[PDB]
């Protein structure tokens, strides 16, 4: 059975106006700004952007890759697909 989301989990993350996007749940670094309650820090592959999202916007990667893991015209998306598949846990600092 599923657990709660934890840092390291790979997802497709949905934001208004964007396709479901390859992403991961990030750790909060010591001394770094925490997310609001019930939100997780989402790191977006390819763009390397962070946003704060709740579970309704987070789709587990394995279950969803067949639907959402296809090339997309949007800036950074295809890079993002490579990242999530090839080195999802690397530093992209």
Image (cartoon, rainbow, N blue to C red):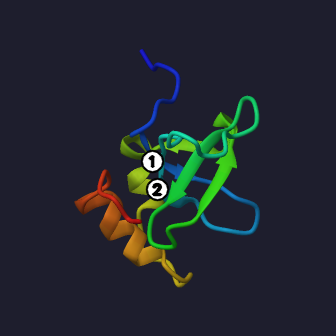
Residue 81 in the image: state x and y as whole percent.
Answer: 37, 67
Q: Residues within 10 Å of mark 2 (few under 14, many from 20)?
A: few
The answer to which of 75 and 61 lies nearer the viewer is: 75
Q: Is residue 82 left or right of residue 60?
A: left
In the rendered structure, find residue 64 and report the number of the disc placed on it. Answer: 1
The answer to which of 26 and 70 lies nearer the viewer is: 26
In three-dimensional space, the C-alpha distance between marks 2 and 1, rounded to whole angstroms, equals 6 Å
Classify the position of the N terminus by image quarter.
Answer: top left
In the rendered structure, find residue 85 and report the number of the disc placed on it. Answer: none
Identify the secondary structure beneath mark 2. Answer: helix
Residue receiving disc 2: 67
The answer to which of 64 and 33 lies nearer the viewer is: 33
Vertical placement of residue 18 versus 10, above or below: below
Which residue in the rendered view is the most extreme toward the front?
31
Classify the position of the C terminus by image quarter.
Answer: bottom left
Residue 11 in the image: state x and y as whole percent.
Answer: 47, 47
Which residue in the rendered view is the most extreme toward the top?
1
Q: In the rendered image, which quarter is residue 56 located in?
A: top right
Q: Is residue 41 left or right of residue 85?
A: right
Residue 41 in the image: state x and y as whole percent.
Answer: 59, 45
Residue 53 in the image: state x and y as whole percent.
Answer: 68, 45
Vertical placement of residue 13 versus 29, above or below: below
- Taking the spot 65% from the left edge, 55% from the top edge, the residue there is 51
- Taking the spot 75% from the left edge, 30% from the top edge, the residue there is 37
- Taking the spot 72% from the left edge, 29% from the top edge, the residue there is 38
- Taking the spot 41% from the left edge, 76% from the top edge, the residue there is 78
Tag 2 and tag 1, C-beta contact below 8 Å: yes
Vertical placement of residue 13 versus 63, above or below: below
């Amino acid at each position: 059975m599923p657990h709660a989301f934890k840092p390291g989990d790979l997802v497709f993350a949905k934001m208004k106006g964007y396709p479901h996007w390859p992403a991961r749940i990030d750790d909060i670094a010591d001394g770094a700004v925490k997310p609001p309650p019930n939100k997780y820090p989402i790191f977006f592959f390819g763009t390397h952007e962070t946003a704060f999202l709740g579970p309704k916007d987070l789709f587990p990667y394995d279950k969803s890759k067949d639907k959402y893991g296809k090339p997309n015209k949007r800036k950074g998306f295809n890079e993002g697909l490579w990242e999530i598949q090839n080195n999802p846990h690397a530093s992209y600092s």
